[PDB]
Length: 77
DNA sequence: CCCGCGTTTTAACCGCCAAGGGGATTACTCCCTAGTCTCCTGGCACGAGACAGAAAAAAACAACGAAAACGGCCACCACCCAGA
Image (tube, rainbow, N blue to C red):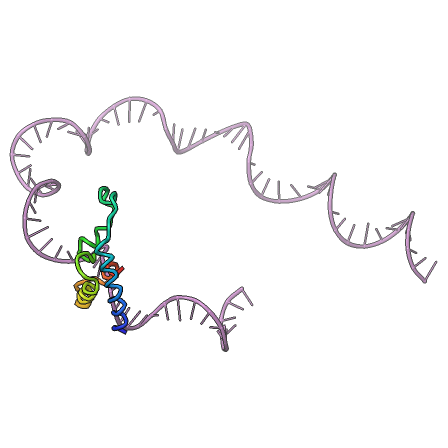
């Protein structure tokens, strides 16, 4: 069950790292501050590195309890 | 109408997990309250005077209790209709 729940994350990780590393803003949310800075202020946004390395790192953070089980949900959302 | 007993359904209860609001505490600092001296004027005691109200007597009226009249219901008689 764990292996099957991580294989999909692997494939989607290739594709989704490709995606996330090119998440464009538009023009007018920044001038008027219309984007969600919440997942960035506490560094849960997946910008900067792999997806099948931040999912596992976040899982570790969650098991140790350092990461809320609610914010992990949004970050994976 | 409410108690009693019985199926049938509902949700209370337990227990377990996850999250965080807010109780509780600590440390810093200041602004508010206690305290005190001097000043005085508001509140109290005393005196007074007069009018609001108690009283009162008398009249008006406004609640309590009998016989006649009117209306309604029941019984009896008369008239009309239906049946034998």
